[PDB]
Amino acid sequence: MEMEKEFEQIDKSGSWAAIYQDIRHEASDFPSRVAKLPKNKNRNRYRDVSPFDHSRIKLHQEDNDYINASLIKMEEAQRSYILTQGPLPNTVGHFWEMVWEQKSRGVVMLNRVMEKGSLKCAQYWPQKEEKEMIFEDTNLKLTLISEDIKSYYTVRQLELENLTTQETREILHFHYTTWPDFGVPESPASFLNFLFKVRESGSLSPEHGPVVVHCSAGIGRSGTFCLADTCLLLMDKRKDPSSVDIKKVLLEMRKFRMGLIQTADQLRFSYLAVIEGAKFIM
Ligand SMILES: CC(C)(CO)NC(=O)c1cccc(Cl)c1
Ligand SMILES: CC(C)(CO)NC(=O)c1cccc(Cl)c1
Ligand SMILES: CC(C)(CO)NC(=O)c1cccc(Cl)c1
């Protein structure tokens, strides 16, 4: 079926939970043996969210190459994304090592450091120009260059230096700051505006390594971001845009990381975002 009318048909019939449970039943199951090794317990935020072995990002290190991060490679859309958990106190150096090694231009953050009164990820970037951060375990230096605070999101320019070679690179930090502590946003307008700002920066384009996107677990809000982006790109590329099937695209993405889209409300929000986005594109 088309999307907008499939949408109203699920709303009128109140069957979002049944649609979402079908997706969960049909989703891929692949091994995640490296994630479950005992030496990696303090590298995982949640025991039930792990990268598959076949698609995990490897650190270029011989001691321990493990990080909780996955490469989502979308062949028809010609887009790639790295989805990862919010960094932990003992993985902030690994996180920036990955950004460096994968040649990423941008980092997309969809959570606040504290939500619901608890810590959802480490404070992993510097908050003042004159107070830079040094990650001694991976030999990197990170400096805040500039910050632009808007009503729904903040964009930061960062300098990452490889202290071994003295090479430097400019990284863009795109921080969506207004996702509610509970539920999903009422309107997708600010989320779509944010997606378009990431696109306009070049961070999603083939002349760079894959964008790094995270929330707390790296599957819910993060899944919503890449699902909406890929669906809108396919609607632009194909002769018949009504052939784009968001459930099929989501199942394709779940070949590369488990659990993408965590609730039926996140599924409905993803439909809403793609529907409204497709009208603005033209
Ligand atoms: C990312 C770079 C190349 C930047 O200095 N660092 C490393 O690869 C690294 C990894 C593990 C340990 C240490 Cl000392 C450096
Ligand atoms: C702007 C320059 C030319 C360094 O001055 N390139 C980068 O900063 C950069 C950023 C991300 C990835 C990689 Cl490979 C390079
Ligand atoms: C340039 C086009 C028209 C794509 O062809 N779209 C946008 O610039 C845009 C901006 C904000 C929100 C949304 Cl959904 C689209």
Image (cartoon, rainbow, N blue to C red):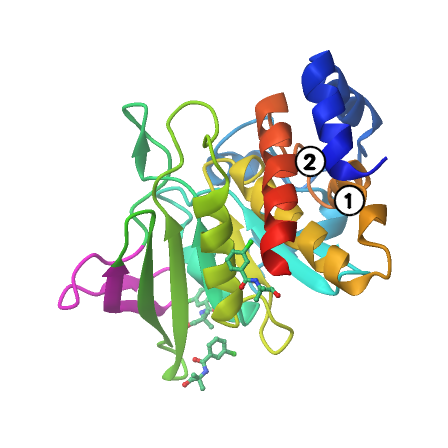
Q: Residue at x 35, y 39 (%)?
A: 178
Question: Observer-nearest residue: 165 or 202?
Answer: 202
Q: Of the residues shown, which amino acid type is indicated by label 1? A: Val
Going from N to C along the chain, the mark reached first, 2 or 1, is 1
Q: Of the residues shown, which amino acid type is indicated by label 2? A: Met
Q: Residue at x 73, y 21 (%)?
A: 10
Q: Tell me the SS state at disc 1.
A: helix
Read off the magenta span.
125-148
The x and y percentages for residue 150 are 28, 54
The x and y percentages for residue 39 are 54, 39
- Which quadrant of the picture is home to ligand 3? bottom right
Q: Which residue is mark 1?
A: 249
Question: Which class describes the residues within 10 Å of circle 1: few (<14), some (14-19), or many (20+)?
Answer: some
**Magenta-colored stretch includes residue 78:** no
Q: Tell me the SS state at disc 2.
A: loop
Q: Residue at x 33, y 43 (%)?
A: 122
- Relative to 151, is 20 above or below? above
Q: Which residue is mark 2?
A: 258
